[PDB]
Image: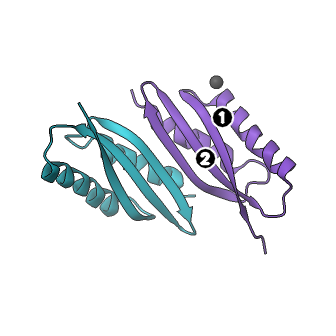
Chain colours: A purple, B cyan
Amino acid sequence: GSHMNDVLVDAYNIAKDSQHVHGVHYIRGRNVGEDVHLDINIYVDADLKVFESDLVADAIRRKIEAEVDHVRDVHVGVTPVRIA
Amino acid sequence: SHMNDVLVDAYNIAKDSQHVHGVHYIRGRNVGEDVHLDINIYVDADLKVFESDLVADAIRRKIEAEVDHVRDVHVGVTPVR
Ligand SMILES: [Mg+2]
């Protein structure tokens, strides 16, 4: 039936403990038929380079797509934060 | 942090409410210790405006009553024919 709960938990848990993630900013799940479309946005250090943040988002995407059932069209966005 | 609990509990409250056809989407945002929650439910297009309003409101009340760590809960509706 609904797979949202599993998708959101498993995806969040992947994102929150990936490298360079200071914390999850937001997560959004939308049901479309049997699929869940997922948008996650992660906080990263404002001083990270673009190439590095691009790799992080892509890794998180790859891992969610590999391990989380019922997911479609996963998007991982990044928000800079100043780290004291 | 508390996101996982907030999303699951709130989704479950919404989905099991009478007059909800299904959950359309759910969004959690972390702001410090708080989670801000937006949830959107599918309802029958023929519900009256007053009725859809009562459903959304009841969901909001229940989530605010039962789900720790939530702030600024918004329940929106999407009509379905
Ligand atoms: Mg896959």
Query: Could you say where residue A39 lies in the image, as x and y percent from the top left?
Result: 58, 43
Q: Amino acid at mark 2?
A: Ile
Residue at numbered disc 1:
A64
For residue B24, the mark is none
Q: Are marks 2 and 1 in contact (CB under 8 Å)?
A: yes
Q: Chain of mark 2?
A: A
Quarter of the image for residue A49 reads bottom right
**Residue A53 shows up from this direction:** yes
User: Quick check: B16 left or right of B51?
Assistant: right
The residue sitting at the bottom extreme is: A84
Front one among A37 and A67: A37
Q: Secondary structure at mark 2?
A: strand
User: Quick check: A22 left or right of A27?
Assistant: right
Quarter of the image for residue B12 reads top left
Are the residues under badges 2 and 1 in a single subunit?
A: yes
Front one among A65 and B12: A65
**Residue B2 shows up from this direction:** no
Query: Could you say where residue A15 lies in the image, as x and y percent from the top left?
Result: 67, 46
Q: Secondary structure at mark 1?
A: helix
Q: Residue at x 63, y 51 (%)?
A: A41
Q: Is residue A83 above or below residue B18?
A: below
For residue A40, the mark is 2
Query: Could you say where residue B4 lies in the image, as x and y percent from the top left?
Result: 52, 50
Q: Amino acid at mark 1?
A: Ile
> Which quarter shows the N terminus of chain A?
top left
Q: Crowdedness of circle 1 by 10 Å Cα count: few (<14), some, many (20+)?
A: many
Q: Which of the two labelled residues, at mark 2 and mark 1, occupies the earlier sequence position?
A: 2
Q: Residue at x 73, y 61 (%)?
A: A80
